[PDB]
Amino acid sequence: TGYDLSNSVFSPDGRNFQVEYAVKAVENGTTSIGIKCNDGVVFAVEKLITSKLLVPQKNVKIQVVDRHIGCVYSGLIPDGRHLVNRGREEAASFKKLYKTPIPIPAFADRLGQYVQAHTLYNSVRPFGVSTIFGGVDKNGAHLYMLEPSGSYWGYKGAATGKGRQSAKAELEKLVDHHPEGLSAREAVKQAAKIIYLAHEDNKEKDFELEISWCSLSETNGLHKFVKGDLLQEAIDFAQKEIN
Amino acid sequence: MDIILGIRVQDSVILASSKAVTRGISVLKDSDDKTRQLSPHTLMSFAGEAGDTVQFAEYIQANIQLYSIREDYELSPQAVSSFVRQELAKSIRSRRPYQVNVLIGGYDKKKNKPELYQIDYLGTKVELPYGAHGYSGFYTFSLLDHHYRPDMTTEEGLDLLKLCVQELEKRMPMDFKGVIVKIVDKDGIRQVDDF
Amino acid sequence: TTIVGVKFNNGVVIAADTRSTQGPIVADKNCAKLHRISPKIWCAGAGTAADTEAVTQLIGSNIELHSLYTSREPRVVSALQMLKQHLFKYQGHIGAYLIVAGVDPTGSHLFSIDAHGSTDVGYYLSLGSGSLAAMAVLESHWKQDLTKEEAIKLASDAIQAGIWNDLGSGSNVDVCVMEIGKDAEYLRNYLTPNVREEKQKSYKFPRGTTAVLKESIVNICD
Amino acid sequence: GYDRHITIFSPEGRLYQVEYAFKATNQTNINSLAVRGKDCTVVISQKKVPDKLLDPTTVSYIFCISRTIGMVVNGPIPDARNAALRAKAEAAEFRYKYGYDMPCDVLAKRMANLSQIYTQRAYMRPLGVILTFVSVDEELGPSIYKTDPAGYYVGYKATATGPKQQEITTNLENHFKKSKIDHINEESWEKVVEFAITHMIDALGTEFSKNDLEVGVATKDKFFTLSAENIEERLVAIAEQ
Amino acid sequence: MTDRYSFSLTTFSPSGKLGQIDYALTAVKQGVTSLGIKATNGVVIATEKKSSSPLAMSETLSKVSLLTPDIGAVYSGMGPDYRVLVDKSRKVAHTSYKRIYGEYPPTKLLVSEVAKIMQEATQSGGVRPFGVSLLIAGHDEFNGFSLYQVDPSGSYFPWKATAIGKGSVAAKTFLEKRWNDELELEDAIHIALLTLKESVEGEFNGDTIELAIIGDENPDLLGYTGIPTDKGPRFRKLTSQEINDRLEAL
Amino acid sequence: SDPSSINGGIVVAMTGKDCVAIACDLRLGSQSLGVSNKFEKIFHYGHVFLGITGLATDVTTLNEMFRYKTNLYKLKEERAIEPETFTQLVSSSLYERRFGPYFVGPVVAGINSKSGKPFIAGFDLIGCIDEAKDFIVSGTASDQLFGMCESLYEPNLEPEDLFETISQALLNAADRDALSGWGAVVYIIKKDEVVKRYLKMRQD
Amino acid sequence: TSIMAVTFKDGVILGADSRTTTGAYIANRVTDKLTRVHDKIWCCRSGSAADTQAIADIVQYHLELYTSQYGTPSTETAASVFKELCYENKDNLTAGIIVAGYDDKNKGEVYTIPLGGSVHKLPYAIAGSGSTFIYGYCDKNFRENMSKEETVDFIKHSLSQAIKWDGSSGGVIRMVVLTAAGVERLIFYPDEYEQL
Amino acid sequence: NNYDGDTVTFSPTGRLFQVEYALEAIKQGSVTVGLRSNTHAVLVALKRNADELSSYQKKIIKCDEHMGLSLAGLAPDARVLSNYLRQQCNYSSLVFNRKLAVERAGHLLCDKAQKNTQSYGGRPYGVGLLIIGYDKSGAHLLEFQPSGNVTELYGTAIGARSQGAKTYLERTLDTFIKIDGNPDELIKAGVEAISQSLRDESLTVDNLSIAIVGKDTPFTIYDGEAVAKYI
Amino acid sequence: GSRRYDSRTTIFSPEGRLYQVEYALESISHAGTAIGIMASDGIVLAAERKVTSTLLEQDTSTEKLYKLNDKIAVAVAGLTADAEILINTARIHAQNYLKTYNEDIPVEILVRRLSDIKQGYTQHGGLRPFGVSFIYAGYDDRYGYQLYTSNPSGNYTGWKAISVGANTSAAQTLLQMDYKDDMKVDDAIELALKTLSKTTDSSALTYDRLEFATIRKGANDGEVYQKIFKPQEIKDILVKTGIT
Ligand SMILES: [Cl-]
Ligand SMILES: [Mg+2]
Ligand SMILES: [Mg+2]
Ligand SMILES: [Mg+2]
Ligand SMILES: [Mg+2]
Ligand SMILES: [Mg+2]
């Protein structure tokens, strides 16, 4: 054996064990989700409060790319920042040459090809993050989830991290109960509920909720963080459902 | 710089080179030796652009001396002249070419013959019985065409050279402050002190 | 140079004069201005002589490799694209003015290329210093639906206009006919309307006329 | 045994990394099939969307490389998309450089050459994919050309790829033994698509809904994929006969 | 990133063997048989077309390749390695010869360039050797007809006749009994077909056999007329029909 | 400061019956000043003869370069280079310096050892091959040589007659050029003997 | 050259003369200055023939690669690619290009790109040496939301006058109609347009 | 074990051992404390000597007039990272006439450390940093780990026995956060914090290092007799 | 990374030997023997071809003896492909010297440069050394006739008579026995063939398993001629000395 000691090496199965090992780093991370809605997308993430000394609201994890795309990830946080930095470079060069802001599927492949490139050589390490991202373009709303292998798909709802299975089950119920569609403001509330429900798998430390959204009607197609009254309203909705 | 002459006789090559270094309206020096010994039996005189001349001469000198030490052997005058020509032929298509004209006087010990090569800054090499660079040739060539014989002695060559310097001192516009004369033969290179 | 190209029924024909000049002096009285890029793609070239030859050989070489790579007969548009991009890259400094013609699986084609890299399409074209004399003939006698023999006549007539009226052009007419479904036929010295008349006198000298100083045998063996 | 980790020869003259890349090909558990008509080239592939949270419209292994060339992949999607982007870039550059559309077989050779390099150069791994290129070439007509991680490529009368490829292959062989010709003797592409689905059904022994399949069709001057309703229309036609 | 493999992957073992070259030759041994025979007025190179599937069109896969109008190549071993070597070989005939001298290289020199390319894959950083042996047949004005074998090491040898690959040992012995210095091209084609039948198991016809010759100039294959000095390629691939004609009088 | 007319010189080649002749002057000057009367402009590599006019440093450099290249040719090819092949090599080598050329007017002359055919060719400073049945001219008296050759020349001259024609072509052309002359050399070339003759000419 | 592009109710029409010159010699009297960079995105070329061809070829390549990845590009996107090439290489280019395309969302659109490489979106654009002579006429006669027949007549009359006064312009009047219906090529000969 | 040869290798449970070993170098380092109010931010550092003949290794470095940090672990790595911060602060001033936000300073350090954890040949930085600053959004304290993780805090501590000070500050949170407009009291709280990490040794005059930045105070460091006030 | 697969071709053993050089020499010891003998009026080069097949084209073949210029030749023992890389370099180097100095390159200068290239592959670059040992036979007007040998280490030495490849130990003893200084070329020809005949691993030494060459001043007056023997000429010289 020894097939798992070097990135880009195929095992006799046809697997890249180093990528599968990067997936273990993602499964260890905190829960993050994405909900696709009527005219946009909603992102939420669990922020474990390690200590009283953490300044609330001041360790922001959701990131904006361009002005219309939001990104959230679970696993090695620095790795996720590296991916977003590249995403921002990709989006800038697309807008530079083609004028129009980068479409979400186009942006999804840019990240995909870049992450896939880090499975091609033994001189680089795969990314230790699964990234949920999306936004609104000329063809409406798109939600994506990208994994260490470079694999990504479009999603109705997406979840990753330590509470992914709990969150997935909760996401599937929304898809079944709302075939016509979920509204942006509703999806924000649901995101809060699901993060709280997914927190059961990480319940030693209590947490801080962070939500963002892009909606054609609610945010004018731009990425915005959910703060103040709308955030507290979403927190309260979630608190009522766990009891 | 300015005047460099060369005469190949029966048994030796004689080089005469002007002593003046003039810049602007001032003769800065009247004892300048415009020559470098490349090997025991090879001497090179030079004239041309200020700075370029000595820089090129010493660069060639270093290379021939390096060769001598590496092989424990002295290159033939023909071999040295070909090396020098190629360096100038490279130089002429560089960003800044060496503007240096040279005469190479050598005694081939394997052939027991004196040899004189005239090479200009373009890398134009010719073997000659007598040579000159610059305006000097316009007086000396015709003079030597008349008085030179291929079987002359070193003493006869020196008298023939005196005749050239006298003509140049009569008809040339500039004061070149006389010449340093050096002889290259079977015994190597020596300088005539009273000219 | 005068060079032309003329399309017909089932293909295309190109022609050229054979004069090469250096200022007012005729350097070559019978030079070949028709170049083979591939078996059925040929080029007529005016401008700087070494440039038209070199650019035609390079693209011809690359076209051969491309043909071998793709297992396909080369197309005129490929030679056209490769030539124009090469010439554009050199901003006119490679003084090649070319009429590119030939037949390929797509059909028969006729193009011209300027030294700066612009290209034309047409049924009849002329380039070079004698192109105005040639074009005058082409504009006077060209018509749609020419036969093979009509197109050759028109093409060579257009070259003749250059030969007689342009001091840059002279000597002979070369022709190449590229017909669909057939081998290209290169007609070297198709017309030779400038044969030198008999000289009035033989200038053969009595042996010993030239004074000689030395003689020697030259060794060419090893 | 480091000769099994990089693309150098084993004592028996084998390249294990290339062999293991072939096994990665079946990791998706999807079977693909390609056939030729008179005027067209049809490629079909299974579409398995296990997760209910996936947007099914974004799950695809068929790619439009150029206006004329289509490509279906057997293997993981990251490597599949890597190959697709390169193929698109290569086909675009070819058109710019040489003034005509890149033929299906030439693109196949080029991609096969790139794959060969990964089998010889150590720092680059092979892609765990098999690429089937389809078109209606303006010179050669309906064309199927297929590439693998060894850098091998060849033209096909018809072909199949995936875990249950052998069943489909022999099924197709037996049809062409019977018909005595190199293609599907049919006028419309619609019926060639129907043939393709029919013979996949027989070979695999499974029934397909409109969302269990994926269809690409190449005609003169365009390659296009079918919608769920285009396939449904096609499934209805098979059932009513 | 970047190729960090700047070191040799082929190195000397204590016994003196170059492992990767030996193993490359082993890959050639597993490869399908190919052969070459030199006649007085031509050269024949032949091989079996091992079809991967009966659905595959074996015409689209050419094992015998034209390098120059007067030079052809065939191989035993790894097909993909051969294909890229043909691409490189065709190009080097232009870049390092035709673009300099205005004519195609003589066989020995083109062979020498291919051998160099294969030698470099044996010493350069981060590459394995090519897993093929080549047989290159060709003609040139001053050397006449010739036949060369190029091995993974980069070594090349001139041959009167030889075989490489699967059943090369038996095929070489067969060729030793039949070869003389008076063989005419048609006699060499006949012996080539006989020798190949021994190593071929299944179907033996013009669709499963690939065969090309280096012989007389072919003006009909030139594609143009008008230049007397250009007389056409000496390389010609025999058609499926032309092979079957000779298999009846076998 | 026109590189092709600083040193001066001429070369001419002619074909005869089963023979070729190539001739050159001996002058090397620096504009008005004559410097050397021993500067030969014709060289040979095996049986292939090359004459070069123009800037003398490039004449020397190209001789050394073609000796270099023909020596390696012979080692690899195991045969002497032929005039047709050498002509192509000269053209390639010159065009390689397309935008920084050698200021030369080379002339190839020789007999193909396989076919027995006499061959001559000329080039411009950048590689354009000028092939001829009759004669090639080069140098600062090229106009004069063109006039002399075009009138004096007739086809299929015998080696001894061809010598007289080419010599009279060079001599009278050189005497109408300030930068050409100061001696002359003529090469008469047959299939397997070459004769070199120095001509007596006026020394002004 | 005299070139123009005009938006109307159903889309946009491009127009051009067919004259290419070197000094006062007409090197080509049947030139096609209306160039396809995509199915329904075309351009009118003016300035250096070599420069505008080289640019159009690069743009067509870029949009082909765009389409392979992201589907049909917008007319604005095509104009941006033209701009990028013209702006960044302004020292080495003599190209005046009018870009015109048809979207189904945006309908007809015209972008003009002068020498410097600036972009200007307009209802209609005129360019080339002959445009100078029809600024007055075109400003007085252009109306928004014209019909196909009205727009054809507007371009025909405009280029007729541009051709009449500009020596650099002449030959035939070519036009390309870009609508939802497809792509239509029109040609008009001297005997028609000269006597307008 | 088999997966700790370099940073480019993941372990089977998804760990990066070289990064974890770099983290270990910080744990061996001398204790340093960081804390802030709404008006000021304070660093306190315990300096370490080789012996009684040697100087005490300086722990605190100034980055700009409004920013600076304290270090624990490999000191040369802190010099490299502080120099990078000095340049980034400087770039912001020269190009934008803008003082670099302490938050951006954190993002920049994160991304610089990260690149050393994904490529072959490199190694992770072997030092932890506590960055304090005062910018347009008031006082700040950041904790840098060479894994790339940067965290904004009211207070913290890194180094050997840092858990004592970290627990203390966690208890004292409500008190010290409201020490506004009083530098000497915020320092006293930090000096009391670092005292919870001492064993057998006590704070002397050439042992203690204090830094402060705030509303009307440039980043300034106190050593020697200037810290005698606080013992 | 890639460190895992690095053989480290340019390192020392604990004993201070270069592994790869030693193993390359071990490879060369299985190659066909080549012998050089320097006489007062010329040099002989003799080499044994590696086990021949009867269908090998013998006349148009070159494996052991290569021409570097008109005055210098080499006998090869080792990988032929490796040798041709080095031979082409040596050929170019000779022409560079001739172009620079207008004189044919002195033998030692050419030998030193080729040996320096070999040395480089043992000290830097991480590549395997060239598995080749040369015997250099040449003439120049300084030292006259010279024999040299170089091996994968890049070390070269001068010889009166020397062998490389297989059975050098036995071959050297035999050469040491019958060689004397006043020897002539034709005597040296005989010694070379006799030595190969006794050291060969074959049953009997025949013309088809040999390459032969002489470098004499046996041209016409004060000039040197290289004679690469044709098959028939080797057949004759083998009969003339009574080996067959
Ligand atoms: Cl390729
Ligand atoms: Mg590899
Ligand atoms: Mg004169
Ligand atoms: Mg005079
Ligand atoms: Mg320009
Ligand atoms: Mg007009």
Image (tube, coloured by chain):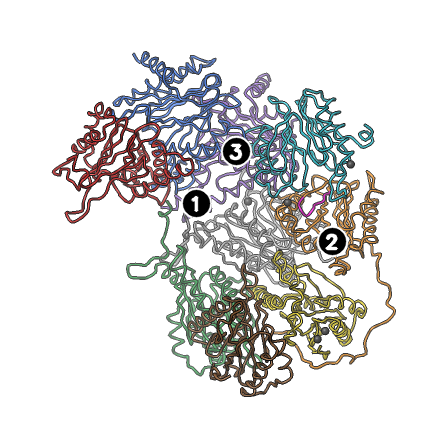
Chain colours: A blue, B brown, C orange, D purple, F yellow, G cyan, H red, I green
Disc 2 residue: CB within 8 Å of ligand 5: no
Q: Secondary structure at mark 3?
A: helix
Q: Hey, which residue is sitting farthest left in the picture?
A: H200
Work out which quarter of the rendered image holds the N terminus of chain F and state it: bottom right
How many other residues sit within 10 Å of disc 1, few (<14), some (14-19) or many (≥20)? few
Name the image quarter holding residue I124: bottom left
Measured from the top left, where is residue F8 in percent x and y? 67, 69
Residue that label 3 marks: A96
Name the image quarter holding residue H63: top left
For marks 3 and 2, give the one nearer the viewer: 3
* E35, above or below G159, in the image: below
Q: With G89 as the anchor, is G127 left or right in this view?
A: right
* G183, above or below E125, in the image: above
Residue that label 1 marks: E2
Residue in the image at 17% along x and 34% along y: H197
Q: With D226 as the anchor, is H92 left or right in this view?
A: left
Residue that label 2 marks: C33
The part of the chain drawn in magenta is C110-117
Q: Nearer the viewer, residue E121 or G179?
A: G179
Measured from the top left, where is residue I81 in percent x and y? 48, 59
Residue C114 is a magenta residue? yes
Q: Secondary structure at mark 1?
A: loop
Q: Is residue H8 visible?
A: no
Task: Identify the amino acid type marked 1.
Answer: Thr
Chain to which the residue tagged by mark 2 belongs: C
Name the image quarter holding residue A64: top left
Q: Secondary structure at mark 2?
A: loop
Residue in the image at 55% along x and 33% along y: D159
